[PDB]
Amino acid sequence: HHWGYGKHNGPEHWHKDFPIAKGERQSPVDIDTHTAKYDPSLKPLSVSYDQATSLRILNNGHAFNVEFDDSQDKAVLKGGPLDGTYRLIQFHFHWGSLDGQGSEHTVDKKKYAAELHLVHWNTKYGDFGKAVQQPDGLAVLGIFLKVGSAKPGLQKVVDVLDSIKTKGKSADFTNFDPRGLLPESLDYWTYPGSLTTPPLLECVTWIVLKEPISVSSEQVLKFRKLNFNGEGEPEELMVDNWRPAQPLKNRQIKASFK
Ligand SMILES: NS(=O)(=O)c1ccccc1F
Ligand SMILES: [Zn+2]
C-alpha cells in the first residue's frame, strides 16, 4: 500500500508513485562545507516568532507536527535568500533509531541524531496548498539536533507525545514558543530543493543552520516511543523517518558566513 519508511515502502520505492523523486532539485542533500560558497550579498535571516500562536500537535503517521495559526502574519521568516514574507505553518522533526543517524541533511557526510524543520509558505501565494505548486513557495528552516545537554524549550513537546502516540491522534497545544528551539547563531547554508517526503514537490528554499541544538538522550528517547501505526494496529516504532541525501545535480549551496 502507501509510502513510508519500511523496506517495502521506503525512500527507494517512492519514485514509483512520485516520479519527481528522481528530479533536478530533490532534498535533502549532503552539505560539503568546503565547496559551499560564501555569498556576501546573503542577508541575515529575520526570524519573527514573537506573536506565534501554536494550536495543536498531530501524529500524522510519518512524524508529529506542531501546527500554528497561519491566517495572519504572526510568525514569519524573511531576509536571507528570501524575497517576501513566509508564514510559519508547522514544525516537525526527523530522527533515528540510534543517536548516530536521524538527520536528513548531512554536513561533510556527518549525520545528526535528528533534524527540526520549521515550515513556512510564501504569502504571495495565499495558502500552503497553492504555495507548494510554486518554485519559491516554501522556506524550510532546518536545525540539526545532537545528543548532549537537554533543550529546555523542547520539553513541553516531549511531554505531550504520550497523548499522540499513534497515527491520527492530535492534542491541543497552545502557547508554545518556537523561539526556544533555535540555536544562538543564525548562520546558514541555503539551496533550492524539495519536500523530503511525498509528494516531494520542488518548492522549497532550504535554509539550514550551521549551529546544532543539543537535546538530551531522554528527550530523543521519547521521540522513539511514538508509533507509525494507528491505535489497535500492530506496533511499529516511529524511528528512522528520514530520507537519505539525494544528488546535488546542478545546484550550488551558498553560505551566509565564512
Ligand atoms: N520535511 S519537509 O520537506 O519539511 C515537509 C514539509 C511539509 C510536507 C512535506 C514535507 F516533506
Ligand atoms: Zn521535514
Image (cartoon, grey):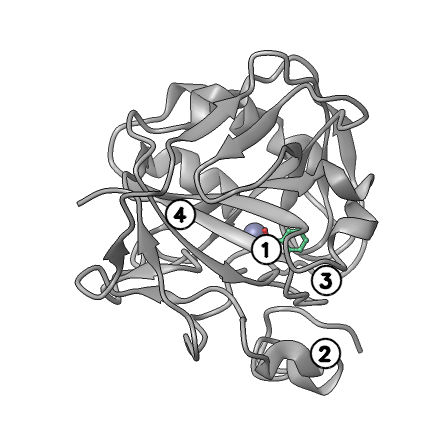
Left or right of 32 in this view: 177: right
Q: Which residue is mark 2?
A: 18
Assess disc 4: are there few (<14), some (14-19) or many (≥20) residues with their C-alpha within 10 Å of its C-alpha: many
Q: CA distance from mark 4 to mark 2?
A: 25 Å
In screen coordinates, is 55 left or right of 28?
right
The image position of residue 4, as x and y in percent, is 66, 69
Q: Is residue 169 above or below residue 55?
A: below
Distance between mark 3 and mark 1 Cα atoms: 35 Å
Residue position for label 4: 208
The crowd level at tag 3 (other Cα within 10 Å; few <14, some 14-19, many 20+) is: few
Q: Is residue 18 left or right of residue 75?
A: right
Give the label, 2 or 1, closer to the camera: 1
| Residue type, label 3 | Pro
The mark closer to the camera, 4 or 2, is: 4
Tell me if label 2 and label 1 are in contact, CB under 8 Å: no
Few, some or many residues within 10 Å of mark 1 (<14, 14–19, 20+) = many
Residue 108 picture quarter? bottom left
On the image, numbered disc 1 is attached to which residue? 204
User: Cβ(mark 3) to ligand 1 < 8 Å?
Assistant: no
Relative to 235, say whether 9 is above or below: below
Name the residue at 65% across, 12% down.
Answer: 175
Residue under the point 23% across and 42% down: 257
The answer to which of 231 and 95 lies nearer the viewer is: 95
* Marks 3, 1: nearer the viewer: 1
